[PDB]
Length: 110
Figure (tube, helix red, strand yellow):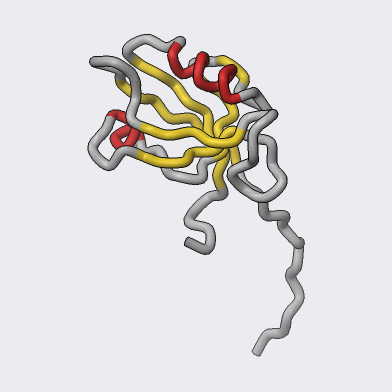
């Protein structure tokens, strides 16, 4: 038959993703947690991660998932940004709101 020959060890690590949310009123329907200064959401990571995802909201539609490490928002860099910074960013967005989250291709643990 055949034997183990191939190899090529591939590295695994969350990837960058971009989602588009719609704003027809007020703001979106998600929750953020972390931000420099306050406690992190995931381990020792001073990043802005999703704390909640309104089941029946605009985000849910976009395809946002709790735990997603926000990287950008409407172009704004939410990299290790303070709560305010993040919050503000969110506030700063029109109808269509683009949010760049970080996640690994597929479900992780659960």
